[PDB]
Image 1 (tube, rainbow, N blue to C red):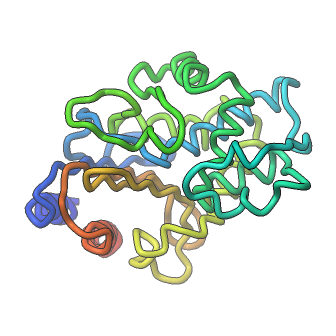
Image 2: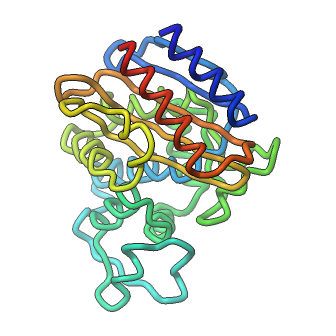
Length: 263
């Protein structure tokens, strides 16, 4: 909607930074709204959904098991590991790790899962085989969120990420038990409160994953809809701002408020 686009543009002014935005019809996949659909932004923790998508693809192929339990060391822990910190003695299942990565944005959890599939290069390979020749993961946590200007490492485009999230949630790429599990994990997102969720009325469905990074980087991907069912995909990214976390949050929430008001 034209007015959501207006608010997007206003968000650039307020942050002094680029903003990427796309809006997809979940069914047809048709583009309903866009701004800088094809510029590159840092993915940030937003990749963790793509990651668990790769993990599920393997479960479907007999090359992994959600129940498999993984043990790790104090030396494996990186910055921000809210749930992995608490399981040094007993370890965690692939299931629990994917939940922790998507749901709590747990960093060690994501790393552990990257090891599972052969690292960043293999995630990028997986993406490529499904027709996304743009999205690319290059480093591990926490260094993938450095967002050096012009650096194309660890980036996607709003249009790609969205087309890709749709294929994962909706397409024949995963089995339906797996499509369901992916979206169930996003729906259970325990962070992202200050974002799109704060503009969502009761009764609306939302499954999402947020991302934060260096140099004012912030973003979110989501499937959302009225009447307890999702019907659109929204992808939002910004990088470059010098604004507070709170301030970058606010601009996000307000974009959502427009999206919803003008549904």
